[PDB]
Amino acid sequence: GTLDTTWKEATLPQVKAMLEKDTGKVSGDTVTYSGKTVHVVAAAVLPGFPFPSFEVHDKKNPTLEIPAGATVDVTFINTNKGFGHSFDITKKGPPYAVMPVIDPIVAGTGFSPVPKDGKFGYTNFTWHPTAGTYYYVCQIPGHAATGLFGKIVVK
Ligand SMILES: [Cu+2]
């Protein structure tokens, strides 16, 4: 397939507005989405959160519960200075090797731009999942191995 390798730029307040567009409901460490079309907004290492992690709806690496047959619009933002993290959805689960074995990637991005001059790289892609469990992971060597992944349950 093709990975999403095209990115836009957002200042911090734009990043924050976008994060607030996530349509999920938080419960504990889970984010549950409902409806025909859902909007997942994920960020790589929001300030104040542990490295390395993804934040979705203000939670760290949460399990995303998505309805089978939904159109999933994912916005991925990299807010972590010094890194070009990716966001890739795969059926291969953890733990991951330093070079993570995650092919085939069912939907996702290439490496993001590193933050520069108050601007953060972000991108939008769409996913049409069938029922199953998937994981969202970064491909930068060692990141997935050190905790940069989360789970998705589609049902
Ligand atoms: Cu990474």
Image: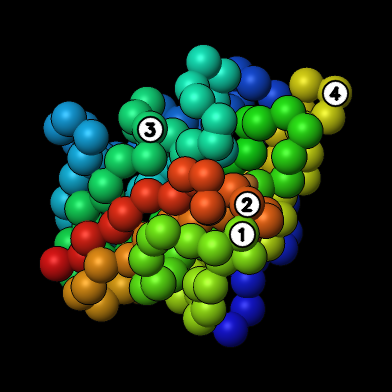
Residue type for callout 4 = Asp
Q: For residue 83, what is the image quadrant?
A: top right
| Residue 152 location (% of width, % of height) | 29, 57
> Spatial distance from mark 1 to mark 2, Cα to Cα?
4 Å
Crowding at dot 4, Cα within 10 Å, few <14 / some 14-19 / many 20+, comes out as few
Residue where numbered disc 2 is placed: 142
Q: Is residue 73 left or right of residue 132?
A: right
> Spatial distance from mark 2 to mark 3, Cα to Cα?
18 Å
In the image, residue 137 sits, relative to residue 56, either above or below, namely below
> Spatial distance from mark 2 to mark 4, Cα to Cα?
26 Å
Q: Residue furthest right?
A: 117
Crowding at dot 1, Cα within 10 Å, few <14 / some 14-19 / many 20+, comes out as some
Picture residue at 48% right of the left edge, 22% below the top: 49
Query: Which image quarter is the C terminus in?
Result: bottom left
Q: Earlier in the sequence, mark 4 or mark 3?
A: 3
Assess whether mark 4 and mark 2 are in contact (beta carbons under 8 angstroms): no
Query: Which image quarter is the N terminus in?
Result: bottom right
Q: Earlier in the sequence, mark 1 or mark 2?
A: 1
In this rendering, the count of numbered labels is: 4
Q: Earlier in the sequence, mark 3 or mark 1?
A: 3
Q: Which residue is more in the foreground, 11 or 152? A: 152
Q: Which mark is residue 98?
A: 1
